[PDB]
Image (cartoon, rainbow over all chains, first blue to last red; front, side, top):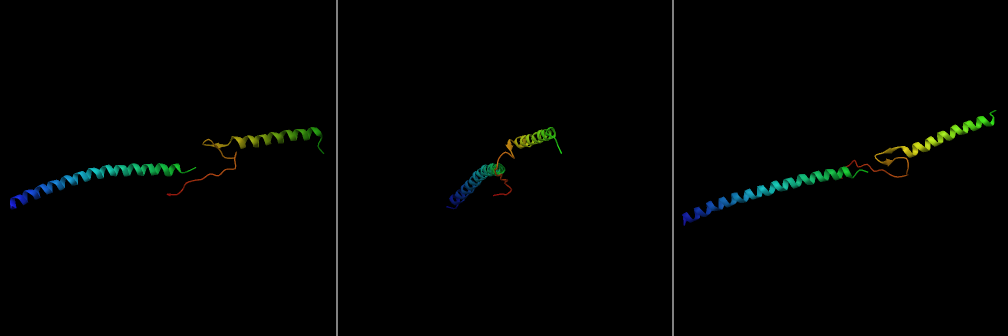
Length: 50
Length: 49
């Protein structure tokens, strides 16, 4: 039983690492989406002038 | 004490300068917008919102 539990915990740790990785990738993509929206807002603030 | 010829010359030069005023009224432009050719309003955005 102890061996089974240990092996399961090792797999759990590895899976959690993989999840952290996918979260990191998503966060990077969202960071660029944020930068793009910031630039568009800047352009709009410029374009508001008459 | 001015004869008719003097009045005619003065009128000619006055009309010349009036035409100059009208021309500069039409002429003065800024980025394709005539500043003095209409009674419009011009908004300047100086705020973040």
